[PDB]
Amino acid sequence: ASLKVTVGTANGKPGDTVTVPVTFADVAKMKNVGTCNFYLGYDASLLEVVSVDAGPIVKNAAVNFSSSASNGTISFLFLDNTITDELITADGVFANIKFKLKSVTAKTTTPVTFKDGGAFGDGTMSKIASVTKTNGSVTIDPG
């Protein structure tokens, strides 16, 4: 059993803005998610982060979620130690990253990857044993 966290894929032309979702799977199996923090790396010479927003599975994001993107790194933080009804309990989109694509000489697929580890805790304040991380990417097709 393990929590599956996956970065999606997007494809676009330089100048386009695309959305790359980060999804959680097998949440219920893992006794839910009460806290987490991880980081994704992206190539700042190819992509520009326009914004990062909590997804549908995050309840009361204004209070429980925080994200910051600085050069090449995006930090994701979720913390709900006390309100049971605001715990992450369903599978789905945890966050949506909007990237603006920069120019490229030729078609390029650049990875959006998990970096610097992180931490994941269940609703019971216990470490989530196993987390399967899957990187995503953005394809920039010259135009």
Image (spheres, helix red, strand yellow):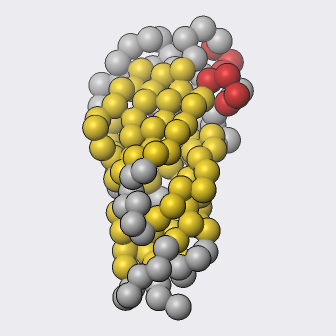
* Quadrant that contains the N terminus: top left
Residue plotted at (47% across, 80% down): 103
Image coordinates of residue 78 in percent, x first then y, are 53, 27
Q: Where residue 139 appears, x then y in whole percent? A: 44, 75
Q: Position of residue 2 (x, y in %)?
A: 34, 35
Check the image and report above or below for 117 versus 129.
Answer: below
Q: Nearer the viewer, residue 116 or 22?
A: 116
Query: Against 122, is 96 above or below?
Result: below
Residue 25: x %, y % from top left: 47, 42
- Where residue 46 sits, quadrant-wise, is bottom left
Closest to the observer: 57 or 100? Answer: 100
Give the farthest residue toward the top. Answer: 82
Viewer can see residue 3: no
Which residue occupies the foreground of this view, 24 or 72? 72
- Is residue 66 left or right of 25 when viewed as pictured? right
Rendered image quadrant of residue 3 = top left
The residue located at (56%, 66%) in the rendering is: 100
Number of marks drawn = 0
In the image, what residue occupies the spot 53% across and 79% down?
14
- Most foreground residue, 45 or 3: 45
38, above or below 99, in the image:
above
Q: Can residue 122 be seen?
A: yes
Q: Is residue 58 left or right of residue 41?
A: right
Q: Residue at x 52, y 71 (%)?
A: 101
